[PDB]
Image (tube, coloured by chain):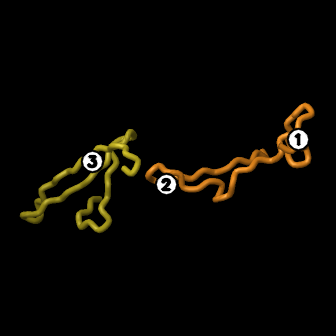
Amino acid sequence: DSMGQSYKLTTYYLKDQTQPNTWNTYYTVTDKEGEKPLNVAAGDAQTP
Amino acid sequence: TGHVGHTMKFNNDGTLASLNNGQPITSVALGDPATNTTPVDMNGADPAQ
């Protein structure tokens, strides 16, 4: 971060079944409270 | 409760941003009861310090 605190960024890769040659990527940021998902502003991959 | 302090603001890189909204920090007279609700008992010394 700006203050020099280190955080764990976990990137998850999912292979799309509906569309061939398509992959879905998600980001999660891990703090002392747990693993909080990180959302993309204009991403075209959405989950319920 | 009537206790007046000063606010210190800092930037995201950790450096000082502002002090007392840019105003110098001057405290009220220590032993003058007319300016402070809790006068310091200065035992005959200068009350306007």
Which of the two residues, B14 or A42, is positioned nearer the viewer here? B14
| CA distance for labels 2 and 3 | 25 Å
Q: Closer to the observer: label 1 or label 2? A: 1
Residue on which the image places disc 1? B47
Residue on which the image places disc 2? B11
Name the chain under label 1.
Answer: B
Q: Colour of chain A?
A: yellow
Q: Residue B48's spot in the image, x, y percent?
A: 86, 45
Q: Considering the numbered disc 2 on the image, is that residue within a helix, a strand or a loop?
A: loop
Q: Residue furthest top?
A: B43
Which of the two residues, B39 or A8, is positioned nearer the viewer here? B39
Q: Residue at x 60, y 50 (%)?
A: B8
Residue type at tag 3: Leu
Residue on which the image places disc 3? A9
Name the chain under label 3.
Answer: A
Q: Which chain is orange?
A: B
Structural crowding at the residue carrying mark 3, measured as other residues with C-alpha within 10 Å and reported as few (<14), some (14–19) or many (≥20):
some
Q: Closer to the observer: label 3 or label 1? A: 1
Q: Residue B42's spot in the image, x, y percent?
A: 87, 34
Q: Residue at x 41, y 47 (%)?
A: A3
Q: Residue A48's spot in the image, x, y percent?
A: 29, 59
Which of the two residues, B22 or A5, is positioned nearer the viewer here? B22
Q: Judge from the rendering whether residue B14 lies leftward or rightward of residue A7; answer left or right.
A: right
Q: Judge from the rendering whether residue A13 lies leftward or rightward of residue B3; answer left or right.
A: left
| Discs 3 and 1 carry the same chain letter | no
Q: Closer to the observer: label 2 or label 3? A: 2
